[PDB]
Image 1 (cartoon, rainbow, N blue to C red):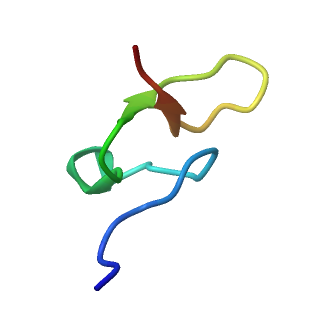
Image 2 (tube, rainbow, N blue to C red):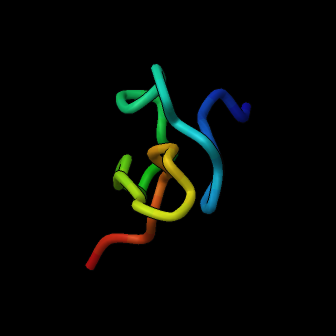
Length: 39
């Protein structure tokens, strides 16, 4: 099924929840870490 945080989503306390292919990246203007696409 689907048990993970999609892309471009807030991951304040869910850094290890980001879906496959994403990483909890901290922002500056947003002030809230979000799952970003990794290479």
